[PDB]
Image: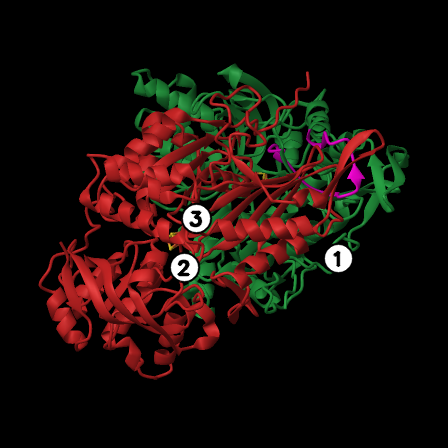
Chain colours: A red, B green
Amino acid sequence: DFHFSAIFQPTDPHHHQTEFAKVEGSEKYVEEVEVFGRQALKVNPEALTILAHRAFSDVHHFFRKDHLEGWRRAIEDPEASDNDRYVATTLLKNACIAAGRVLPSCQDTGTAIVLGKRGELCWTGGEDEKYLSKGIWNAYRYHNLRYSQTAALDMFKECNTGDNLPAQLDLLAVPGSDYEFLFIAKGGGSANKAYLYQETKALLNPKSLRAFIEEKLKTLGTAACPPYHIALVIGGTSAEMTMKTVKLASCRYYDSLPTTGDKYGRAFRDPEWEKIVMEVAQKSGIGAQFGGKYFAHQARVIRLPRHGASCPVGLAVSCSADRQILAHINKSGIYIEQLEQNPAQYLPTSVKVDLKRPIDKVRQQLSQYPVGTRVMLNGTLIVARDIAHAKIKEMMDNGEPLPEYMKTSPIYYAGPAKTPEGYASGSFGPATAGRMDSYVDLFQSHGGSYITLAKGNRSKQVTDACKKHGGFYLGSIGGPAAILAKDSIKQVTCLAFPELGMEAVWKIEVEDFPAFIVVDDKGNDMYSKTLA
Amino acid sequence: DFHFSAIFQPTDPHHHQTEFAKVEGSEKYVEEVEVFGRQALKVNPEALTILAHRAFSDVHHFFRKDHLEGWRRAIEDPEASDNDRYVATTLLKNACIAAGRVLPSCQDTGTAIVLGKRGELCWTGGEDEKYLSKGIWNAYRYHNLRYSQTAALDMFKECNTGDNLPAQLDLLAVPGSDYEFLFIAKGGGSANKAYLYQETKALLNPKSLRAFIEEKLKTLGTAACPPYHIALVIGGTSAEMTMKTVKLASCRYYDSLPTTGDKYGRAFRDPEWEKIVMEVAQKSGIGAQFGGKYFAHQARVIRLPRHGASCPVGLAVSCSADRQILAHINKSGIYIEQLEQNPAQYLPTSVKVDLKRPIDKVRQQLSQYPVGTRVMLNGTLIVARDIAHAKIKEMMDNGEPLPEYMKTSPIYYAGPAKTPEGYASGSFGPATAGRMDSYVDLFQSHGGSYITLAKGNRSKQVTDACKKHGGFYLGSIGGPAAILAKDSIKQVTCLAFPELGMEAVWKIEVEDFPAFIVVDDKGNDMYSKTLA
Ligand code: SF4
Ligand code: SF4
């Protein structure tokens, strides 16, 4: 009567559909042995350091085929909007620059996540986390990446760890004698667009589920640099299991799951509802960041079993910095997923805005144009993101003035990666605007932040503030951090709060920096139709 | 220089502070060996079956000391309300019944969750998931528990799996040669009160965090059978990592973490903010289900590192069916956490309502009393939960009438566990009322569901419906499923939809069933002040 049924039964559990390259000479790190009649594998733990180092280096310079194919699809589709094609062309040209192996594809080189599966008879000596962390440390220390991890000294006092550690190290015990891996360099913006909903049986019918999808996709907005890989998980044995599953689905880790359920509750991919998600995504008009058809590359929908009283649902995306690498260690050595090293093969007006003027003259020029106008910025940007905004608000709460540097120039919400030797700037694209929304009305009321520059749709309070104080929000393209650094950024200087690392206040000189007028000084918002 | 720092550094990683009992004779399942100069442990996988069977049997009849102490604190504290003391006394008497090892403490015997940590040199043969699942299968099949897992045949077509499988099996690879475990029998209601919030640096100040905590605690309501163990996690390396941590925090799995952070981003428990959570919970007035001080047993607050662009937050509770057990296998055999087998040592006015009358006469009697009135129900209840409600609405959408049996008696939202031989009923406590909110107005408009009986606060639409149609919502005490079955439930018969198992429509006869009038027929709601 008892029948064991694993929840996840991929038909390709070892990811044979993926192309791997062997690390040259890496068979010296492994030795196949036989113990008590069973095949086992001795692994020098230095293999873990070597593997993690290469994985978290390569992944910042190359992309998978299904990601690149999506950008080309947005360029070639007659139904794509002009903005769709402009964004996709820009991201692909960004990928070409990143493939030069100097500049990472995004300034947000992400959190280092390791999903590892160590076989019962795979013997590393047991210090896997230290050796994996050293390889990750090497990758972020010795390459032009970014230190993004924020340590809590107490509940509220924070500092940058200075090395992009700690990593998320999920090491599982599995059958066999191999060691299998998924490495993820997970950007903060798309990590923030991982959502958990606690729903009920009332959701589980065609009309309700379709309306639910239409509603929740809109809450993703453009804040995580679409086109998205959209993952949706219906059900699950706990909230944390639902959210792990939707993360892995967004990495296409579960693509070989069955497509039908059974009486034992096995997980399955639902291609019919993937099609509906894609139909909703396309018909939404949200587009590849600035209106159109290419809100989404593709969709993954996984249906899970559930406690009768429960229906957790997970929604998550992979962003333009779509960065994951499969790997495994076996008797022949270290194998790492082969990414596309020639993205160029996928490759098939605007208003000049002089920033080198009094800020009021820039505001006057911007006021002459409607939202949706493509602009090109030339001059000085002041760079400030989450922590700098919080420190400045705190200064003003203690009676100090809004600093002079918040009043002279557009505010670019951004944090750079490290500068390559002989380069003017490391990768330096925008951060998500919505996280600074609570500061806009306050700062504008105190004579600054009249012009902000970032990516993503913003809340109504920012539209209201810009109308009240004569402000503007400019939307940069999201994602193309390498080409912005190579072509547009000419000088970079740390202005204030240097202890914050990448979150310091910066002063940068910029030429031909593209952006769209998203919010004007009249109550208009170019996302008000598609995202409201 | 590189410095490895594990995120979690418990001072008691093997839980020496917990009392364990050895399974008698269990050293026959293990054998110490040495291979390549290293000590390894061969473990007969049968040990996993034995351990999982005992864990998921014991945990349904006994509780930890800190849970039982919380109930006694609600009885003996002069600051506890009369309802606080009444609910805590009821739950404690329920625990004494459950300690008889026949009836489980709750009808929702939960999802079977296994956190396992298999040492590198702990050799089981590798079929851990099957052997653990057989032990879980044994516990739910051969004891008076409940089959709560719902399989998806397709996106919308569902069936009960009939054995409470699949389990959630999280088997981690760790150093050493032992096998350590945390077993959790997680109720659906408290699983549903696990929430993920995507927040920002703007939250991370005392005023904002305190306001956030006050706001989110109210959204827990009474829907997961308080007094709660409240867990709050601020930060994390991903949503799924944050939600896993808040689950484990709620099981007091991380109680021995350090209490200060460092520049490497280690996790820490924050006793100052645990105190603040307890102050918010107590001052909320929500109480142990029906107004008072004992919303919470205790609090756990864990501060985690974060990507600078990210601040995931997790909030979750352990409910009155607080069910976890630690265990480990080592060279000496199988050890399992010792729970309290004599809960009685912690043990230191109502309106009679005859249900055997026309439902309209019952409504006239209830109409004479204000919300908060305690009642004792005597007569027939019609039992129907999520699936039966969805099926009946589906019938009505296809033009069929609301069935007569939905109009003759109050509707009790509940699903019983299996009936012990010679008993009138298995454990049979209430389900969460809020999940049926979308049906009340519809059913009342068609002449039924005028009186519902469940637990938890309900949404505004139910208050409006009861005022419009002369209805009432009665709140049963949440949690005391064993004593309700032993003392109050006298007869159980399946009335309709027998294929649904525990989710069929039942007709039950009841005596001295306690409840509170939560929503009356006048727009009043006894949670309108505390859960506004
Ligand atoms: S900036 Fe955009 S592309 Fe880069 S990590 Fe954030 S969401 Fe992804
Ligand atoms: S105690 Fe309440 S919330 Fe917990 S499992 Fe039982 S009915 Fe559900």
For residue B378, side relative to residue B335 (left or right): left
Q: Check contact, mark 3 vs mark 1: CB within 8 A.
A: no
Q: Tell me the kind of residue under disc 1.
A: Asp
Question: Can the viewer see residue B468?
Answer: no
Q: Is mark 2 within 8 Å of ligand 1?
A: yes
Magenta stretch in the rendered image: B107-129
The residue shown at (53%, 24%) is B151
Q: Kindly state the secondary structure of the residue where label 2 is placed.
A: loop
- Across and down, in percent, residue B399 comes to 29, 16
Kindly identify the amino acid type of the residue bearing the numbered disc 3: Met
Magenta region includes residue B82: no
B354 vs A318, left or right, is: right
Left or right? Give the position of B290 relative to A48. Answer: left
Q: CA distance from mark 2 to mark 3?
A: 53 Å
Label 2 resides on the chain identified as A
| Residue matched to label 2 | A107
Mark whose residue sits in front, 3 or 1: 1
Circle 3 packing at 10 Å, graded few (<14), some (14-19), many (20+), is some
- Residue A201, how many percent across, how many down? 43, 30
Would the CB of label 1 be found within 8 Å of ligand 2?
no
Question: Residue at (51%, 20%) from the top-left corner?
Answer: B504
Q: In front of the other: label 2 or label 3?
A: 2
- Label 2 crowding class (10 Å Cα cut-off): few <14, some 14-19, many 20+? many
Label 1, on which residue?
B12
Q: Are marks 2 and 3 on the same chain?
A: no
Which kind of residue does numbered mark 2 sit on?
Gln
Residue at the front extreme, as displayed:
A25
Of mark 3 and mark 1, the one earlier in the sequence is 1
Chain hosting mark 3: B
Q: Separation of disc 1 and disc 2 at Cα?
A: 40 Å
**Image disc number at residue B526:** 3
